[PDB]
Image: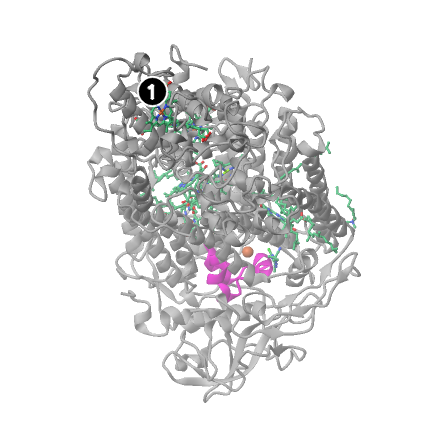
Amino acid sequence: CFEPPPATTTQTGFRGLSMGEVLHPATVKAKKERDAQYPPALAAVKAEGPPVSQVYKNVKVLGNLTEAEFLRTMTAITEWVSPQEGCTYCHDENNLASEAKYPYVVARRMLEMTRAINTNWTQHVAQTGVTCYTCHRGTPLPPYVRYLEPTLPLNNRETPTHVERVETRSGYVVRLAKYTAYSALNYDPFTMFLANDKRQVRVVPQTALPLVGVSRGKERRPLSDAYATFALMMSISDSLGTNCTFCHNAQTFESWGKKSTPQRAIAWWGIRMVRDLNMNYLAPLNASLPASRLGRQGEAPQADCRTCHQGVTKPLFGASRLKDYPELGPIK
Amino acid sequence: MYHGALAQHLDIAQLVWYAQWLVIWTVVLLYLRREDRREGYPLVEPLGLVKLAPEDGQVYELPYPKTFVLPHGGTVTVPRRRPETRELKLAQTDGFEGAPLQPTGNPLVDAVGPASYAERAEVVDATVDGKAKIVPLRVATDFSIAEGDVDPRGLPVVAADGVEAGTVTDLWVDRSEHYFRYLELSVAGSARTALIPLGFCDVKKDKIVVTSILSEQFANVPRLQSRDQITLREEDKVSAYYAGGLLYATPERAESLL
Amino acid sequence: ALLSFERKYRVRGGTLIGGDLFDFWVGPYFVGFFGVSAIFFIFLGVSLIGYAASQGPTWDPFAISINPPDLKYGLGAAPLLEGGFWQAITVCALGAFISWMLREVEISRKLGIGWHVPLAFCVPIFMFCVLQVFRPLLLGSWGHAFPYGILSHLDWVNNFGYQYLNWHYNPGHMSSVSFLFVNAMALGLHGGLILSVANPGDGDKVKTAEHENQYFRDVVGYSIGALSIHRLGLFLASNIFLTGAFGTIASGPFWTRGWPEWWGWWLDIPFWS
Amino acid sequence: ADYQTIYTQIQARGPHITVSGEWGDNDRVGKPFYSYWLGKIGDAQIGPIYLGASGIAAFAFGSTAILIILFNMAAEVHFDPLQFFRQFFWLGLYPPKAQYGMGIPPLHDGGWWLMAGLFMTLSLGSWWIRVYSRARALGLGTHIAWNFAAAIFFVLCIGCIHPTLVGSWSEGVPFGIWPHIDWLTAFSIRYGNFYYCPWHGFSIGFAYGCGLLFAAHGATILAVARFGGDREIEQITDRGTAVERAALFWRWTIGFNATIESVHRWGWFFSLMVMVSASVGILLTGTFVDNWYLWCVKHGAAPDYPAYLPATPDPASLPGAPK
Ligand code: BCB
Ligand code: BCB
Ligand code: BCB
Ligand SMILES: C/C=C1/c2cc3[nH]c4c(c3C)C(=O)[C@H](C(=O)OC)c4c3nc(cc4[nH]c(cc(n2)[C@@H]1C)c(C(C)=O)c4C)[C@@H](C)[C@@H]3CCC(=O)OC/C=C(\C)CCC[C@H](C)CCC[C@@H](C)CCCC(C)C
Ligand SMILES: C/C=C1/c2cc3[nH]c4c(c3C)C(=O)[C@H](C(=O)OC)c4c3nc(cc4[nH]c(cc(n2)[C@@H]1C)c(C(C)=O)c4C)[C@@H](C)[C@@H]3CCC(=O)OC/C=C(\C)CCC[C@H](C)CCC[C@H](C)CCCC(C)C
Ligand SMILES: CC(C)=CCC/C(C)=C/CC/C(C)=C/CC/C(C)=C/CC/C(C)=C/CC/C(C)=C/CC/C(C)=C/CC1=C(C)C(=O)c2ccccc2C1=O
Ligand code: HEM
Ligand code: HEM
Ligand code: HEM
Ligand code: HEM
Ligand SMILES: CC(C)=CCC/C(C)=C/C=C/C(C)=C/C=C/C(C)=C/C=C\C=C(C)\C=C\C=C(/C)CC/C=C(\C)CCCC(C)C
Ligand SMILES: CCNc1nc(Cl)nc(N[C@](C)(C#N)CC)n1
Ligand SMILES: CCCCCCCCCCCC[N+](C)(C)[O-]
Ligand SMILES: CCCCCCCCCCCC[N+](C)(C)[O-]
Ligand SMILES: [Fe+2]
């Protein structure tokens, strides 16, 4: 079980602190090739004539687009999400305004969510932005999603073994380990941290001595909170294909300033972004999805850091189509 | 308010850091470093033409004497004044305090440098039940060589010079620890045995090789006073004799290795 | 000046090199050629430490730190203040350690005893080289070595560990820790027992070799015997680094993921997957 | 070269020795048997072993602890045999995940962990007694029992006393291979980086020092095995050229030296202190220090480095930052 030299190493901290990335060149190249499948931008169309708001019948989101632009978007959407299936994945063959099929309405919300990320989560996605492809990767079900319990394989394009199957109780500890970089940490950071804003990630005191009043008996957070936080960080690390020192100087995890890299602030924003999407776009879709989409407690599949990043510190190595599809945001 | 805070700036842990260090240097300097001085002290030196002092530092660095009561009777008290009365065939090579000494005779038999022994007791080391501890297998009858190992009785002993120097006649066993410690050999062309500690022996199937000394030098290996017994001091004499060969068997052995 | 029994052992001879030239004592210390070079390098290395430290801000001992160069300088010579001092000091340190070791051989020769101690001493020099020299060569930059600072060298160990997510799952480390823990217990047991026999309490008699063997036969069912616990201890101790060296070397040049994932070779056997 | 110091060239066999206890000579069970291979690098006789009450007691409790742990572990892979064997390392028996303060946790949330912790404690107690008694029985001092006590106390510190001191069972050490390891990091993270705990440093200093000392002691005795240096008791009561040579080796190298007895004192002490320092550090943690790095920072200890990548403000403190 070993990976041969050379390793690719970077520096993310002051010399002598052994901070930085440690990359196996072959893995990087293999991920590069997978992400290289990002379809290139459709040729630019000239905006002739009326907004489709006038022209078409049931266009809510992209109503201001001229027709040519609009069909350009519809084409891009098709090759990002449902290329195998074609336009009819979401449309009634004979009535295009028809909302008959759930992919239509789900796709309508996803146009909204997508323009949300690109307009409002600028502090995370910056000027790279996302598109339907960032998550979907050419299939309607995105390959990396989370339910309210751990599931395996992480890539839902792979076929589960018996033990992996969520119904197989004997395989629980492994479903959890594969989510936390193989640790034995008995916590699921997804449901604890990313599904909603209920829990506080920070667990480390900010004073040298114990403050009288929060430091004894039931006043205290249980130590199990520090395990969870560690589990989450194992997960975030494995999700971005990186290590702690990509973000922290481990001298003082709890400190920012010189003890934290810029990417930690960005990750801080991403935790907030992921919670927004889950709480406000993705989780509600359990209303609009077939039962076959939903998990064991009737939850829609939702997003963690892997859903976009899929093992790279910038999703798709920072490829952007933002200037090519302004429909999708930022929306002034 | 904070748990542990004692004053403006001062807290429990910080005071304990100071106690920890104090406990450590106390045990190290005042205890352990004085236990280190139960042998060899007080330091010997040149002498002064006029001096009269119970020199203070020599008192302060010593612990109080302890006495071991010995299992088979007697006691031993350390530290104690344990001077070396024996004459040493050595001469200063140069004048200064740090100069090494040279042997002026045969260092092997003079017992100087790596050939020195300790003035151990002239007593036979005993087992727990009072018997002699280290005895030849001629005496140690209920003992044996484990099946699988060379029995050396019969084998030739071959000295550093490549020359056969004698013939192994017996093994001496430690009956307290069940462990061979010496081979005994008939010395070639002499009417004597020699013990040779097992550490100086490369045991082959066909011979026993001893590189510490040339065949010539086996003749002068220390002799025991009895034949089926050895005293603590004799063990020391025998062992030291071969050890001294490592520096002294030939002229170039004391000189630079390379 | 001399222990009561010392004078008779203080004979010329035994040198690896130099011969009579440095064959003498300064106080209790034997000098010899390597005494001379040990001292040369110490003086160098300590001088550089001072000069370097003076160019820094802090003179607080805990906070002083002399660090290797940025990774970009690779295996090349870095500016003095930017890794160069560290490079110099590392050479002096190696010069001092090896001198100390060869000096120990010369002392062993003069006394007619085995060379086991200078040998045992190669293990920590070796492990120093793994950290400071070999692993950086494999990764291609001096900048992966550890800084010279009482506390800053702990910040390196910390970060190096967390580069691989959880360094505890490193099988070389697990082996290393186990030897660190056994050896500490064994030294307690060996030390405790020799004292218990020689110091029975009240006015009872010093006990015997047979008693030592009986105690451990009684307590754990095996006594390894008097010569062999010294061999064991030298083994257990040495294997702290001899096995550890592998976990250190593997991290980076031969494994780039977190260490828990390495155990996938077990967990993911498809037979039970 | 002294091959004896590598292995025993010729093994001696002789009649089994027994040194009589002041009691319990009749609880020694088993027939001594000999191993030729063992004999090559140690004493060849395995066994007999003394039984006794404290020992049997120790086994009883120990085994009960183990049963509780393994049964909860089996529950974890839902009693699937093969998944049990597969996942054994990852499987654990955890303390309260919830804050019950010092309330007896429910069986499912730490109740079972306490149980096991209790029986293990009694297991250790019983064993300590065995270790203490055999010494007394054989007319020996009790230095070993006193070194062991320190070790047992450390375990109580991390298992019991620290949880009690801060008032939460949630902080105890889980039972399990990886789980007891994950605790190390959970515990260090919560208390501000154990590298910056002075007693963690003392402890390491002594653990490293035990490696230094046992390598140097062991090597020193092998190096004078030719002079019977292994026979350490009689080298104590009647100094021989072995320990004169050992002592002078060390004097000539480092400038001072021990005796053959005192070096075992140095060793006993270094070993003891690993466990003593460690406990003190645990007693101070949570009770009086919350974040060891900040405590160090409070007192001027901590190093500080230039930014390399740009200094990064806590976004949470920004104007307009969400929560
Ligand atoms: C967050 C990171 C962690 C980490 C990271 C870590 C790293 C990165 C490495 C270790 C290594 C090691 N760790 Mg781990 N560690 C260990 C224990 C150990 C050691 C057994 C082992 C070897 C130490 C070493 O290389 O010495 C080195 C000591 C040397 C080289 C001494 C040289 C001395 C020189 C020869 C002479 C010095 C002379 C002075 C200058 C002279 C001064 C003169 C005065 C005195 C007169 C324990 C017991 C634990 C526990 C209980 O949690 C732990 C936790 C962790 N370690 C953390 C999880 N550990 C090493 C290893 O072996 O990994 C497998 C290693 O590479
Ligand atoms: C891979 C992991 C490593 C590691 C991990 C480690 C940890 C995690 C900890 C230490 C600690 C310590 N380390 Mg580090 N370390 C040290 C030295 C030290 C001491 C500052 C201190 C106590 C060590 C001890 O008692 O050993 C046993 C030896 C004994 C008892 C004999 C006395 C040795 C003497 C105390 C050495 C003092 C060295 C001087 C400061 C050096 C100055 C050199 C010149 C100027 C004279 C040296 C000299 C080296 C070298 C040369 O390799 C080294 C390598 C390493 N340490 C590795 C990089 N070490 C502890 C500490 O408290 O840090 C501050 C601690 O917590
Ligand atoms: C990221 C996490 C870290 C960490 C967290 C950590 C914690 C949280 C603790 C330590 C502690 C200690 N650490 Mg640190 N650590 C250490 C080394 C050490 C030890 C010297 C000391 C623990 C004492 C011990 O031997 O326990 C092993 C010995 C034991 C457990 C004795 C057991 C005795 C018992 C009687 C045996 C019983 C066995 C029976 C068979 C039981 C069977 C029962 C059945 C029935 C179940 C090194 C050398 C390093 C390096 C090189 O990086 C390091 C890094 C780190 N540690 C990281 C910073 N470390 C302890 C300490 O000193 O804190 C102050 C401590 O509590
Ligand atoms: C597996 C086996 C082990 C083992 C074995 C043995 N260990 C030995 C022997 C044996 C057998 C000896 O024979 C020899 C000795 O004589 O014993 C008294 C020795 C010795 N073990 C020392 C330190 C020690 N052992 C450590 C570890 C183990 N030991 C492991 C555990 C550690 C750890 C763990 O950190 C330390 C710090 C010295 C006291 C002594 C060398 C003196 C020297 O070499 O003099 C020569 C050099 C000097 C006096 C000063 C040199 C200063 C340089 C030039 C300038 C500074 C350089 C820089 C690197 C500083 C960095 C500081 C920063 C990290 C903070
Ligand atoms: C600094 C010094 C240290 C130090 C010191 C010392 N350490 C000592 C002593 C000293 C001095 C002793 O005198 C004592 C001893 O005796 O030594 C020979 C002992 C010990 N250190 C042990 C383990 C250890 N030390 C560690 C650490 C350190 N130690 C630190 C470093 C570590 C670490 C590193 O993690 C470990 C793991 C044990 C071997 C031993 C206790 C046994 C016990 O307490 O027994 C308790 C009893 C049991 C567990 C019984 C159950 C066993 C059975 C087989 C289970 C069967 C299950 C089955 C279901 C039943 C079926 C029945 C059938 C008939 C139907
Ligand atoms: C003055 C000058 C410039 C001179 C020129 C000559 C010269 C080269 C001098 C060198 C000066 C220098 C550089 C000195 C530094 C000396 C050093 C490196 C000291 C380190 C001392 C330390 C920290 C040791 C750590 C280990 C330790 C805790 C030891 C204490 C106990 C001892 C002394 C153990 C050694 C020891 C062991 C291990 C035995 O087994 C044994 C068995 C039987 C009898 C004696 C012994 C014995 O003494
Ligand atoms: C495939 C290339 C494809 C075509 C062709 C297509 C066309 C299309 C039109 C012209 C409309 C307007 C119909 C009307 O009058 O309301 C329209 C609107 C939406 N589409 Fe579409 N569409 C194609 C493919 C896809 C795919 C693959 C999906 C589902 C992922 C999809 C979804 C939608 C949605 C939602 C709308 C409403 C958009 C809005 O602004 O509200 N289409 N499509
Ligand atoms: C980009 C504007 C975009 C579109 C269009 C889109 C469509 C879409 C569809 C058709 C579904 C339903 C698929 C099904 O058959 O059930 C769907 C579901 C999910 N999506 Fe999506 N999606 C767009 C963008 C994004 C982005 C940027 C992400 C990731 C942040 C994302 C994620 C998901 C997830 C999660 C689901 C729910 C699980 C599922 O129903 O398959 N989408 N999307
Ligand atoms: C690598 C496995 C790793 C560890 C360990 C780690 C730890 C850690 C801790 C202990 C905290 C708590 C801080 C506190 O209590 O104040 C924490 C917090 C954050 N982390 Fe982290 N972290 C690890 C890895 C990573 C990586 C790779 C990144 C950046 C991509 C990262 C980021 C963050 C952020 C952001 C926080 C704060 C969370 C919040 O405020 O909500 N960490 N980490
Ligand atoms: C989940 C909480 C999560 C983490 C953690 C995270 C981190 C992260 C980092 C550190 C960066 C910056 C890397 C760098 O500067 O080198 C980064 C960048 C982007 N992310 Fe992210 N991210 C998390 C989650 C998500 C999710 C769910 C998505 C997709 C909807 C997403 C997207 C992006 C995008 C796009 C970027 C790239 C910005 C760029 O500069 O190229 N992230 N993320
Ligand atoms: C009852 C109340 C109210 C209070 C009690 C207070 C009390 C005394 C509590 C004590 C708590 C304690 C001491 C907890 C300590 C926990 C610690 C330190 C645990 C540390 C490590 C645990 C580990 C490594 C356990 C892992 C798992 C095992 C060893 C598996 C067991 C397997 C076997 C032994 C194999 C058996 C078969 C073999 C003999 C062939
Ligand atoms: C002569 C002293 N004998 C002796 N001494 C010691 Cl320290 N240990 C043992 N035996 C072990 C190491 C234990 N405990 C059993 C594996 N025997
Ligand atoms: C706290 C641990 C359990 C205590 C009870 C264990 C059995 C006690 C046996 C004592 C035997 C007395 N003896 C013979 C050693 O003196
Ligand atoms: C960091 C662990 C504690 C270190 C303690 C080291 C003690 C060795 C001191 C020997 C002092 C020698 N002398 C001659 C000055 O006493
Ligand atoms: Fe010993």
Magenta stretch: residue C195 in it?
A: no
- Please say if A152 is above or below A283: below
Question: Is B180 placed left or right of B221 in the picture?
Answer: right
What type of secondary structure mainly makes up the magenta span? Answer: helix
Residue lying farthest to the top in this orientation: D319
Nearer to the camera, A134 or A248: A134
Expressed as whole percent of the image width and height from the top left, the position of residue C142 reads 27, 42
Quarter of the rendered structure image containing ligand 3: top right
Question: Chain letter of disc 1?
Answer: A
Residue lying farthest to the front in this orientation: A94
Nearer to the camera, C230 or D72: D72
Quick one: SS at disc 1? helix
Expressed as whole percent of the image width and height from the top left, the position of residue B85 reads 49, 62
Magenta stretch: residue D243 in it?
A: yes
**How many numbered circles are shown?**
1
From which residue to which does the magenta span run? Answer: D219-247
The answer to whether residue B85 is seen in the rendering is no
Q: Which residue is mark 1?
A: A118
Name which residue lies at 55% across and 82% down: B151
Q: Amino acid at mark 1?
A: Asn
The answer to whether residue D208 is seen in the rendering is yes
Expressed as whole percent of the image width and height from the top left, the position of residue D224 reads 48, 63
**Which quarter of the picture shows residue D74?**
top right
Q: Could you classify mark 1 by the number of other residues whose Cα lies within 10 Å: few (under 14), some (14-19), or many (20 or more)? A: many
Name which residue lies at 47% across and 18% down: A280
Question: Is C32 placed left or right of A292 in the picture?
Answer: left
- Please say if B211 is above or below C227: below
